[PDB]
Image (spheres, rainbow, N blue to C red):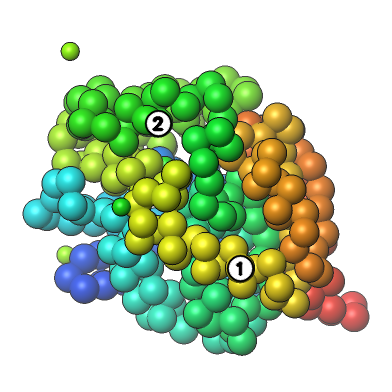
Amino acid sequence: SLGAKPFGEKKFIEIKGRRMAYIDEGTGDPILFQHGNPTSSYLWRNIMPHCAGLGRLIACDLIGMGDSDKLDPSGPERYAYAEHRDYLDALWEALDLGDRVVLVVHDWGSALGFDWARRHRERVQGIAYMEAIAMPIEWADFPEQDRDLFQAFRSQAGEELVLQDNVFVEQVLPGLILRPLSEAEMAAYREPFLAAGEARRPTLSWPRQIPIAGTPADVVAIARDYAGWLSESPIPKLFINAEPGALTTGRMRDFCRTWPNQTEITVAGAHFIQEDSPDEIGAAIAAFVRRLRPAHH
Ligand SMILES: [Cl-]
Ligand SMILES: [Cl-]
Ligand SMILES: [Mg+2]
Ligand SMILES: [Mg+2]
Ligand SMILES: [Mg+2]
């Protein structure tokens, strides 16, 4: 259903000195749901129930996000892709996931999960993705309506826009959900970013890592590598397409449609499509997993 309640209470593991938070429910091989910017495990609350009894249902909060601890010191060099990967790789190792993981990914969760999959391919049973950073892009490929604002985040304007005015949370997020959010929903998204200043840095560092027009070169190289790998990987895939969508449209969507061993559905939504079409998304994921894990009830 739609609904503002969280899916479970947070659990905690110590990673590199910092407590990291994650949702963990059920038993069996993992189904690992990974949010991006500026969300948390909360993004998946109405999707995870569809997988009840199909696996161990896990949704991690990235470092500095959700209920995971903030890094200190923080500033413009903090919360880059590589640092998020360092923490997330360690958390995923700590969770004792085994070798039949189904990844369910969105936004920067897809960049992180696609790279992890490339590096751990024998451990990935299937990949469900939506509104993903599937490859390096050009500014022409970026949604027109928020193009100027994302170039501003990437400029020195970003500190005022995000650290002081919290634009990513307060404007971009609700602007890329078709339906109006309730107070309680918006409160869950605001919670990690209530405080002005470096508490909000993850939401500014993230748009500064998007691989656009060859910059930043280090993330472009990472995405070029997972794009090349996914396009010839035999791992089963589920592409949850969106209309109108946002990022996984145009050239990127065409590229994703070339990937082998893939199923597709289309749901209504812009970018944070989990808030518009959770039951359609969840049902597709559950069907995918049932195929991958035949129960013979
Ligand atoms: Cl971003
Ligand atoms: Cl660069
Ligand atoms: Mg209690
Ligand atoms: Mg501590
Ligand atoms: Mg001014």
Mark 2 element type: helix
Label 1, on which residue? Answer: 228
Ligand 5 position by quadrant = top left
Ligand 1 within 8 Å of disc 2? The answer is yes
Question: Of 38 and 61, which appears nearest the observer?
Answer: 38
Relative image position of residue 71 (x, y in whole percent): 18, 56
Relative image position of residue 192 (x, y in whole percent): 30, 42
- Within 10 Å of disc 1 (Cα), the crowding (few <14, some 14-19, many 20+) is some
Q: Please, is residue 274 above or below residue 257 in the view?
A: above
Q: What amino acid is at disc 1? A: Gly
Q: Distance from label 1 to label 2 (Cα)?
A: 26 Å
Tell whether 240 sits left or right of 228: right
Could you say which disc has been placed on residue 125 in the image? none
Relative image position of residue 244 (x, y in whole percent): 70, 30
Residue plotted at (32% across, 27% down): 152
Question: Can you tell which of label 1 and label 2 is closer to the viewer?
Answer: 1
Residue plotted at (67% across, 39% down): 249
Q: What amino acid is at disc 2? A: Phe
Q: Which of marks 1 and 2 is nearer the N terminus?
A: 2
Q: Determine the image quadrant of residue 199.
A: top left
Q: Report if residue 192 is visible in the image.
A: no
Label 2, on which residue? Answer: 150
Q: Please, is residue 46 above or below residue 174 in the view?
A: below
Residue plotted at (38% across, 80% down): 94
